[PDB]
C-alpha cells in the first residue's frame, strides 16, 4: 500500500520537513499504520499515517526499508543509545529518552525520572508497539508507565488511559538535579512537576550569587531551588496555588527556607514592585507560551516586551536577567529583537552572558522549525 | 570642555549604543580626547572623542566622573579582572584581555599569548595612555607589544608602527590549547596565527571521532590540529601556501602525522570532491568574512549558501558539519536561514548539535550590535 502526496507535499518531504497535512495527500491506505510515501512513482519517505487526521503524514525515514516496523524500532534503539551514557553516569537524574520528531520518532515521547520512565504515544501506529517500547527501555529502568491521557490522542482515535507497562510504578520519585532534588508526581491527577526542557538552564543558574532574586512564572519552583543556593532571598511568583504548593514542598525537601512563594499575576506584580522601589540582583522570566498560533505573534511580542521591560527596570547594576520563551512562533530572531527593544527602552546596557535553548535530550531539527520552541538567554546589566 | 549632541545622537546614547557619528555632534573640543557628552544641559556619558573622524563619539561610561582618564583606566582594570581566573589556572593559554566596545574600552584590544600581550589601539586617546596600559598589564604578563599598524588608525590621524612597551617581546611563542599547541608569530611581517575568537569552538571539536575530516578555510590549521586526535585522516584546505606552511609546522610541533595540507580554492575543491564521489565523517567551514558592509550581504549570502550546500553533500549519514561566519552583517538570523536553505536544497536532514559564537573573552553587548560578529554552529546529518 502507498501514500500519494501532491507537489506541495513532495516539496515538503524533499526539503526534509517531516509533516504533510491531509489536504496534500492525494490518496492513501484505509487504516492508520506505517507506509511508504510517493510523489507519482518517486519514493520520498516512510511515515506514520492516519487517514482521519489533519496531520496525516509524519515521516521517520527518507530511504526505503523492507520492514517499516523494524525500521521504526531501529530509530527507537538509536534514540535510546544517545542517552545511554548519561543514564549510567547520572541514574537519579531526569532526562527525556525520546523526543518525537526530533528523534525521528514522531508521535512518541519517553521521559526518565530517576529510573522510572513515562511513555506518551500520540500517533496511532505506536499503540500496538508499546510492548516493544517497554522492552527496549527495560535495560535502563525500574518501571515504565503508559501515560496516554493527552487530549491529542483523541484526534488519532485513540483511547485515553494511564496504566503501568513494566514493573512497579511509584506515586512519587525524587530526582537529583545538580545540587538540589525535586519530587516528581507520577499519579494521573497530579502535576508531574519536572519540566525537563529547562533542566540545563536551571543548572546554569547555580553560578550566580547575590542578595535578592525574583523567579517570575515559577511553576514548580525549579529555577528558585537553584537560585536559593546562591541568593539570600528568592521570591517565587506564580498564579497557580497548586504549582506553588509543589514549589514549597521541593524547597522543604532541600531545606531551603530562603525561598518564599507569592501567589499573584506576574504582570501586575512586576509593575507594582517597581512602583514601590523594590530592586533585585537577578530576575528569571520563564513564562508559559504567550503565542499559541501564528496569528498571536504581534500581540505576544508586545506582552513579552512589557514583562521584559519591567524585569530589566527592577535590576541593579551588575544584575542578571535570565529570560525565555517557549512559543515556537516567537522565533529566535523575534525573541532577541524583543529583548533588545526592552533593554533600549529601559536605558540599560546588557552584556550577553549566554544564549541557550533546548538541551541535548530535546533535539531540534533544522529542517523542521516546529521542533525548535525554547529560547533561553542570560544577560548582565552594565 | 564638553561634547554636545543633537536629539538623534542623544537617543542613540540613551538606548545605550556606544557610538554617535559626526553628523549628530553639534559641538565639541578642538582636539581628540576624553570628554563628557551632553544633550543640552543633560549629562549622557563619558566618551573618547575625535573632532576629525566620522565616528566622532565612542562612549565608555554612562555616569559622570571627576577624572575621565581615571574612569577609563578603571574600566581597563575591570576588564583585566574578568580574565584573572583563567590566566591563573591556564598561564600558557591564549585569551583576549580587552575586547574594545564589548569591555567598554572603545578603540582598544589586547590579546594574551602564553604570557605575552599584544596591544592594538585605534582611537586617538589611547596613544597617550599606552604607558599606563602597559603598567596595568604588568602584573599579568612577561611582555607587552604595541602592534599599532592597522590602517584604520589613519582615520584617527595616528602613526603606524609596531614597538615593545614592556619586557622583551619574542619573535614567536607557543600557546597551549586543550591537547594541542600552536605557534604564534609576534613579528610585524608575519601572520600571528592565533584566531582566539575560535578557541572554544576548536576545543569543542575534540569530542568527535571518525575516519576522515575536512577542514576548509583552514588558515593556520587550528581546527585540524584538534581533529587529528579523533580522526584517522584530516585534510586541511586553504588557498594560502604561507598559511598551510604554518599548519604543517603546527602539526609537526604536536607530532601529528595524520594531517595533510592541500592548497586549493575551497569552492572548486568541494565541488570536485563531490563529483569524485568523496565522502567525509566531518567537515569544518570557517570562511573569512564574505560581508564587510551591509551592501555585500545579498551576494555574500549566496556565497555562504554554496559552500555550505557543497559541504553538506560531502557528508556521510551521521556526518558532522561545523559551520561559521565572522561577517557581522551576515546576522545570526540570516546565517541560520542560510544553513537551513542549504540543507533543504541538499535533501539532507540536519540535527542541531550546538549553536555557539564568541567566547566569554570576546564580550557581546545587546545594545551595541556591531559587537556580535561570530556565529558557529554544529549539525549532524540524519
Ligand atoms: K503526573
Ligand atoms: K604577527
Image (cartoon, coloured by chain):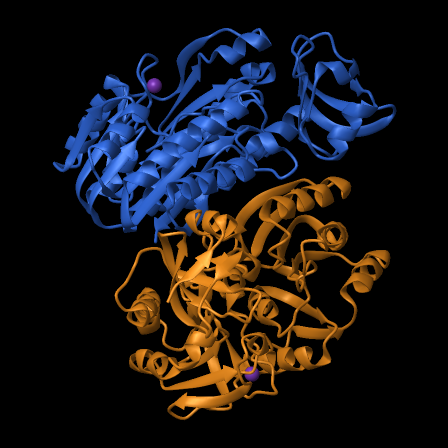
Chain colours: A orange, B blue
Report the number of discs.
0
Is residue B308 among what the camera can see? yes
Asked if B363 appears above or below A362 in the picture, the reply is above
Is the C terminus of chain B in the top left, top right, bottom left or bottom right quadrant? bottom left
x and y, in percent, of residue B364 in the image: 56, 38
Ligand 2 lies in quarter: top left
Residue at image location 59% in from the left, 10% down from the top: B156
Residue A337 lies left or right of residue B98; in this view the side is right
Q: Nearer the viewer, residue A28 or B30?
A: A28
Give the side of residue B246 with respect to residue B68, left or right. left
Q: Image quadrant of residue A337?
A: top right
Percent across and percent down for residue A333 are 60, 44
Residue B5 in the image: state x and y as whole percent.
79, 20
Residue B49, quarter of the rendered image? top right
- Up-down relation of residue A5 to residue B276 (above or below): below
Q: Is residue B180 above or below residue A89?
A: above
Q: Quadrant of the N terminus of chain B?
A: top right
Q: Can you say whether B171 is above or below A159 in the image?
A: above
Where residue B186 appears, as percent x and y from the top left, is 32, 20
**Residue shown at 21%/49% (left/top)?**
B210
Q: Is residue A255 visible?
A: no
Tell me the residue at 56%/34% (across/down): B103
Q: Quadrant of residue B33?
A: top right
Q: Nearer the viewer, residue B69 or A159?
A: A159
Amino acid at each position: 500500500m502507498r501514500i500519494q502526496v501532491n507537489a506541495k507535499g513532495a516539496a515538503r518531504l524533499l526539503s526534509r520537513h517531516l509533516w504533510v497535512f491531509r489536504r496534500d495527500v492525494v490518496s492513501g491506505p484505509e487504516t492508520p499504520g506505517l507506509y511508504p510515501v510517493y510523489w507519482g512513482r518517486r519514493f520520498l519517505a516512510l511515515a506514520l499515517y492516519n487517514p482521519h487526521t489533519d496531520l496525516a503524514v509524519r515521516a521517520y525515514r527518507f530511504a526505503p526499508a523492507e520492514d517499516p516496523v523494524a525500521a521504526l524500532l531501529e530509530n527507537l534503539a538509536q534514540a535510546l543509545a544517545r542517552r545511554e551514557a548519561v543514564l549510567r553516569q547520572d541514574p537519579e537524574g531526569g532526562y527525556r529518552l525520546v523526543h518525537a520528531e526530533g528523534d525521528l520518532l514522531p508521535g512518541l515521547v519517553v521521559d526518565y525520572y530517576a529510573g522510572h520512565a513515562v511513555v506518551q504515544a500520540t500517533a496511532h501506529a505506536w499503540e500496538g508497539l508499546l510492548p516493544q517500547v517497554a522492552e527496549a527501555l527495560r535495560p535502563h529502568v525500574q518501571s515504565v508507565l503508559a501515560k496516554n491521557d493527552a487530549r491529542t490522542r483523541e484526534l488519532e482515535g485513540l483511547p485515553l488511559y494511564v496504566r503501568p507497562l513494566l514493573g512497579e510504578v511509584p506515586e512519587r520519585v525524587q530526582v537529583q538535579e545538580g545540587r538540589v532534588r525535586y519530587l516528581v508526581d507520577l499519579r494521573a491527577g497530579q502535576k508531574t512537576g519536572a519540566y525537563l526542557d529547562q533542566r540545563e538552564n536551571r543548572l546554569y543558574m547555580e553560578r550566580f550569587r547575590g542578595e535578592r532574586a525574583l523567579d517570575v512564572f515559577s511553576y514548580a519552583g525549579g529555577f528558585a531551588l537553584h537560585l536559593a543556593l546562591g541568593f539570600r532571598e528568592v521570591v517565587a511568583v506564580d498564579s497557580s496555588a497548586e504549582a506553588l504548593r509543589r514549589a514549597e514542598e521541593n524547597a522543604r525537601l532541600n531545606g531551603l527556607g530562603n525561598v518564599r512563594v507569592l501567589e499573584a499575576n506576574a504582570f501586575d506584580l512586576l509593575r507594582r514592585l517597581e512602583k514601590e522601589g523594590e530592586r533585585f540582583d537577578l530576575v528569571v522570566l520563564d513564562p508559559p507560551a504567550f503565542a499559541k498560533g501564528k496569528k498571536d505573534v504581534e500581540r505576544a511580542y508586545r506582552a513579552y516586551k512589557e514583562v521584559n521591560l519591567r524585569a530589566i527596570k527592577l535590576l541593579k547594576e551588575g544584575g542578571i536577567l535570565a529570560t525565555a520563551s517557549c512559543s515556537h512562533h516567537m522565533t529566535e530572531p523575534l525573541f532577541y529583537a524583543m529583548v533588545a527593544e526592552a533593554a533600549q527602552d529601559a536605558h540599560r546596557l546588557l552584556r550577553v552572558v549566554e544564549k541557550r535553548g533546548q538541551p541535548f535530550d530535546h533535539p531540534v531539527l533544522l529542517n523542521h522549525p516546529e521542533t525548535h520552541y525554547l529560547k533561553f538567554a542570560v544577560f548582565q546589566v552594565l
